[PDB]
Length: 550
Image 1 (cartoon, rainbow, N blue to C red):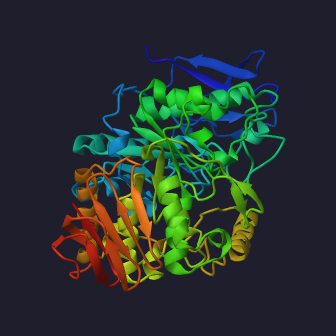
Image 2: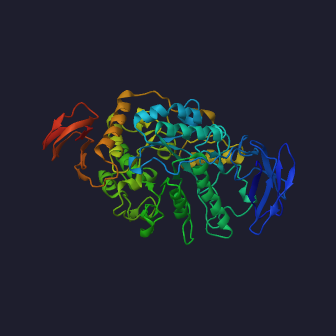
Image 3: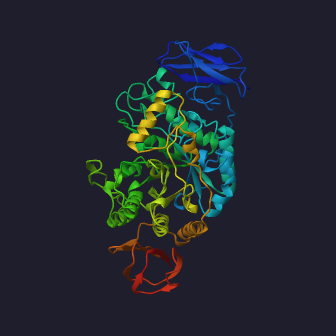
């Protein structure tokens, strides 16, 4: 039949009622654990509903699937037809990721907008797109990390219907979709979980708000909440995989860490998890029989930081830990630069070596939402290095053994900043974030100003020299079988370096210098016209630039 069952976990609350807007108020039945439940025969997609507390105040379903009128508005029923392939066609060894912010990616600012850009993406060579968090957040202008309804697809992005159609059309083109999900904290506005029960940890918390309760009193149910959320995205949206936001901010003292369980869920349904770890700890990524949570891959800032610090000369914040050519070679042959050595930035010994894990347990990047957006003036790397360096940078990571991830626009030479923006309506949060971004990052543009968001939309002004470069770089990566293979040989002089893989070798010349080349090869790609078509073992004097050889 057509009847459906309502479930709300609220141990703090004595007795709660269901409120279907056009219909009546319905008394809910309680159990031992603190779950309120009723089955209603008369409900239909898409009625609006809320829950009314002892307080007599009315809150939206915390496990809501659609919030038509934003965070403080009522919850709406959606069509739940669990259609999903049991497998993803994505081979993680073939993974080229493209990070997208739906709001700013296109003039549209919606899912339909990214759909339109699918052919472009496919043609470029990307195999999967990473969508920044889409869990309902305040208003319509937010990176996604102030999301506060884990099961509800952002209304202004195009809602559930919108996101579903995106994955459907992505699969249709042979593209995969990875969802950025937040399990380490929750948004400061429109979060009503605090009144229901111990969703959040008493113990510590995160720089971005209240952290989840995974290991303390009544944490079973909050563990179920997150694990079922990952189950939900797979079963109801047919998503290929996940990027887990700041896993270092998820603390769990339990016999089996929640991150291990999260992975178990995604692997049960043959999907992929990537983790943003700041831990520099192979445990996140290691096999179970080697004591890891078995997450498929992790972000390695060390790579980006090495490249960035060296090319920019910048040393503020975390860049103080980097700066030398050695750091790049280190990261290129050891993954982590900080693998159990002292960090002046963190004021402690940081990290652990990575052992024999292949390259495909790590994703690398010269740009992403953090490394652009957390800069006060939000400058893309293109503004901080010359055309040559920029090309050398793109070559370094796209030709690395690690999984490369392109930031939206990077590939055609996008020049527009990516600022930090928010769309809170609570005036104290507005006040706090302005001064927060002012003090922490040195942002002069108002995050709550519409113009700041607008200025962050891609221009789509294509630089064809750069765009062609990326396209060929991607193509050669695939053709050379560079993926995962950490068996590379790197030699470095003062202002240059050569990296030699199984089928290729690359020249990375940061200044004019005389280089001893020990390899023969045919030129595949070059940032200049200055490099020979065929080269042989010998000494050469190269100008600043990059060259790839078979």
